[PDB]
Every structure is written in C-alpha cells, then in structure tokens.
Length: 258
Figure 1 (cartoon, helix red, strand yellow):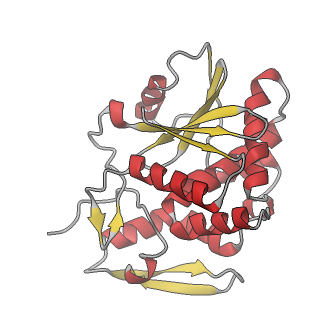
Figure 2 (figure 1 turned 45 degrees about the horizontal axis):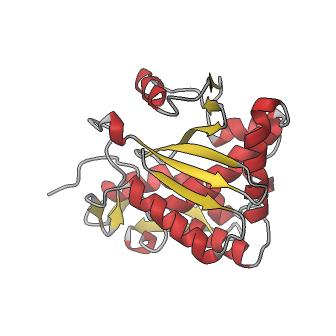
Figure 3 (figure 1 turned 90 degrees about the vertical axis):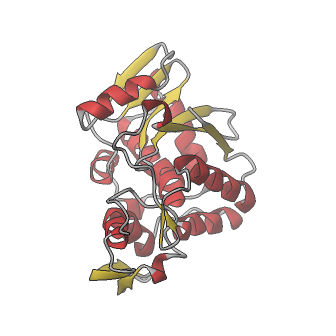
C-alpha cells in the first residue's frame, strides 16, 4: 500500500502543504470530478489492493507511527507502532476482513471495541474537539502518545485525544482545503489552538455536503446546508460554487448524472 511520510520535526507550511497534497493524490485517482471537486473512489467493487494508503508520522523525538487510511472515506482505520498495531472497531464484515490486509507482519495485532468516530473519541478523551488544541506541538505529542501506548506509557484518554488530533490534521485537512488552511496558519505561527466552529461544522457536514453536491441540479442544492463562521454565526450553502475553494474531496455518494 502507498506510503506518505510527514514529520512534525521542523515542519513548515510548505512541508505540510506538500504532505496533504500527496495524501490527496493517493486518496483519489482524479478520474471522478463533479463541479470541479474530486470524489474519492467508490467502495463498491474497489479491489482490496487499492483500499488503503499509509501515512507514516515521525516527530522530533525520533518516534514514528504509521496510520492506515481507507481511501473510500479517508478515515484512519488503525495504526502501527513498532511490533504492535491497533484498529478501530470494524463496522461491517467487509471492513473487518479488509483491515486484516494491513500491517500483515506486525507481531501483535489488536482491534479496539470502540470506533474512531468523534462522539466516541471525545467521550473517551474527556474533551470535545473544541477543547482539544491542534497544531504542530499537539501533533508531535500525539505521535509520542500513540507510540508508547503498547508499553503502558499512554492512558486511554490521552490516546483518544491523540487520535482526535491526528484525524483532524491529516484526514480532515485532506478533505477540506479550508481546514488544511487552518492548520497551515497554526504551523506558520507555531501556535496551538482548538478548532473554531467553522472547522467543527465542516467536519460534521462532510457527508451531507458530499451528497448535496452530487445530487444537486446543475450545482444547485434542493435544500440548503447550514455551516458556521469562525465566530459561530450561521450561514447557508445553496450551491456547489461557494464550496469549490473549501472542499477538496468528497465521499462517493452516487453516480454522476448525464
């Protein structure tokens, strides 16, 4: 499976940008595009040899971890740290069988009983996304946390918090240039900060947005979608046009019309 590398050690806006750009290139072929927005591969009939991509994260502490992302939704399905790999609770028999194709040579394999969805992770973390700082420092720390979990150096709440950081800085950034932009800002000024409502709402609305766009009539939504500004004020999206600079990838929702 394709591997993309990134390190928090000496990270810059440019190195982070190249990284996210590479992730997007491995996530989608670039064949399916709608109203200028790339669509991730349809999971139906997708060969298992093209189902995942690996993201190896390293940090200043010289510690590395490898996350496994599902190309059909950009989810982080699990990770390997040394001789141990951990997977989030599979959701269907298909996903359960699919992850056995990852890190096939790790000595110890484990499957968590919980999922990687935010509601769950925030619950185990004891903190909501809005109270979890993001940036290069948090990422660097998240990597170490993930690394020492198997040896008992990381408590579950910290592990969950770490997943929340990685998922947003990798998967969400890949999905939205607007969140990749938020992370670029954090790196550029070396400031760690929790995601504002604009980031939070985009993250929660990815599925709805992907579907609205794909089912739109020549780009116009049948029903508007409500997002939030940085100050938390509400604003409506009635067309795909306004999302072009915001969403970089969509989950496959339907076949494109003639």
